[PDB]
Image (cartoon, rainbow over all chains, first blue to last red; front, top):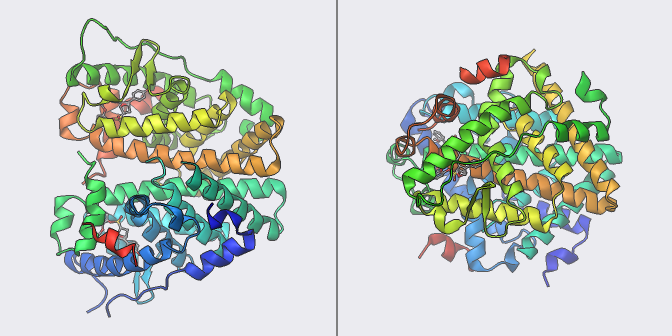
Amino acid sequence: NSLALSLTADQMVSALLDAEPPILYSEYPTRPFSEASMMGLLTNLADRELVHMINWAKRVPGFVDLTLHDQVHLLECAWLEILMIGLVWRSMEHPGKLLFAPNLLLDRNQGKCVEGMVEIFDMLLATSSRFRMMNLQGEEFVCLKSIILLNSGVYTKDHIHRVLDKITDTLIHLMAKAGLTLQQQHQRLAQLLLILSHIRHMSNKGMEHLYSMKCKNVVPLSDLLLEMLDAHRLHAP
Amino acid sequence: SLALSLTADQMVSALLDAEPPILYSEYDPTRPFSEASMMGLLTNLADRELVHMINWAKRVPGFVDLTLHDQVHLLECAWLEILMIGLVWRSMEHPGKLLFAPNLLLDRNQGKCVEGMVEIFDMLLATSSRFRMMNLQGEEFVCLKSIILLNSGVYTFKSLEEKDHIHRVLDKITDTLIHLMAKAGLTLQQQHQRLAQLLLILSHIRHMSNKGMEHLYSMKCKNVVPLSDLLLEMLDAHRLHAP
Amino acid sequence: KILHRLLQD
Amino acid sequence: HKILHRLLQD
Ligand SMILES: COc1ccccc1OS(=O)(=O)[C@@H]1C[C@@H]2O[C@H]1C(c1ccc(O)cc1)=C2c1ccc(O)cc1
Ligand SMILES: COc1ccccc1OS(=O)(=O)[C@@H]1C[C@@H]2O[C@H]1C(c1ccc(O)cc1)=C2c1ccc(O)cc1
C-alpha cells in the first residue's frame, strides 16, 4: 500500500506546496539577442532546474512507490512539460512576457532570436494569459504539475491511476473550499485539464526542435540535458 | 446561438446524429503486406475519412458559428487526433488489435511494416484498452471527439470573441458529460474522477497525434506512396512549423 | 486550400 | 548508465 492514497486532501496540498522547487536566477551583457546567447542562458537555466525537478518528483506523493525504471520513464517523458508549466505559472503577473527567471524576462521579440522558437513563445504566452484569466491558484498549480508528472508517460497501471484520482479529489476539494458551485467545480476541473493537452502539445513541438541536430549544435549541452533530449529523439523519424 | 441553448440530452442527440460512417479499406488478404501497401491502405482510408470529418465538424454545435478561417485552423490542428480517437473507439472490443476498418484488423506485429509505426500502434492499443476498462459509452465518446475539435487549436489562432465562444461551448460539453455520468448512477466523486480520467486521455491522444504527424510529414513517409492533395495540405499545416 | 473550399460548400 | 538513474537514488 502507498502512503499517498492515505493522505487527506489538505495533507496532499501541504505536501505539494512543501515540495515546490525554488525559483532560480539566470546568469547575470544581459538581454540575449542572438541564437547563441539565448540558447546559452536557457540551457544553463534548464539544467539547474532539472536537478531541482528530480528532487521535487521524489516528494510527489506516490512517485516514490514506483520502480526506479518507472520513475526514470515519467521524468524523461514529462520534463519539458514541467519546465513549461512552471514558466507559464511564474509569468502570470507579467502579461505579454515570459519570466524565465526574476532577472530574465523575455518578450516574443526575443523569441525570434532562435529559429522555430517564436511559435512556442506565443503558445506559452497564450497559456500564461489563460491561467491569468482563470485566476489559477497556487494550490491548483501544484496539483496540475503533479498530474503532468504522473500522467505523461503512464501508458508505458493501477497505482498511478489511483494517485491521479486522489489528485482529482484534491482539485475539487480546493474548488469547493473556494465556494464554487458543483457546476462551476466540474467546469473548472475540465478547463484546467484541457490546458494540459496544450501543455503536452507545446512540449512535443518544442522537443522536436530541441533534439534536432541544428539545435543541439548551437552550444555544448550538459550530459544530463542531452540524455533527457535523447529519450524523446529515440522515437523520432 | 444554437449550441448554448441546447439541453444536455439535445447536445447528445445532436452529436450522435452527426456521427460519420465507418468506411471500408481496400484491403486484400491476397496481397500480402509491405511498407508500401500498408501506407497505401492507411492513407487512402484517412483521405476518404477526412471528407466525412469535414461534414461532421459542420454539425458539431457551435462550430459553424466560427469564422471560416477559424474552422480551417481547428480542423488542421485536430484531424489526426480525431482519426485516432475514432480508431481507438471502434477498436475497444478487439483486445490487442486496431480496427482500422471492418475489413482491416491489424495487430502490433503489422505495425512493424512501417518504420517508426509500432511505437504509435502500442500507444493506440493502450488507449483503446484504457477506454475498454472504463467501459467508455458512445455518448461519452462523441462528447470527447467534439472537445478535441474545439480545444486542440484554440490557443494557436474580435478574434478573442471567437475563443470565448469556444470556451462556452466546451463548458456545455463538460456539463453534458457530467449529465451522462449522473444519469448512469455515478456518485458525484465518481463523476468528477471519471471526467478527469477521460480528459487526461486527451493529453495522450494529443501526444500520439504529434508523434505520428512528425513521422507522416517526414520526407520519407511522404514518398512511400503518392499522397492526395487534401492530406498533403493537412500534413503541411503541421510541417510548416517543424524544424 | 481544399479544406477551406470543402468547409465553404 | 543514465545520469537520471544515479540522481533518483540517494
Ligand atoms: C531554444 O529553444 C527552442 C528553440 C526553438 C524551438 C523550440 C525551442 O524550445 S522551446 O520549446 O521554446 C523551450 C521552452 C522555453 O524556451 C525553450 C526552453 C528550453 C528548455 C530547455 C532547453 O534545453 C532549451 C530551451 C524553455 C524553457 C526553459 C526553462 C524553463 O524553466 C522553461 C522553459
Ligand atoms: C503510416 O503512418 C505512420 C508511420 C510511421 C509512424 C507514424 C505513422 O502514423 S501513425 O500515427 O501511426 C497513424 C495512426 C494510424 O496509423 C497511422 C494512420 C495514418 C493516418 C493518416 C495517414 O496519412 C497515414 C497513416 C492511422 C490512422 C488512419 C486512419 C484512421 O481512421 C485512424 C488512424
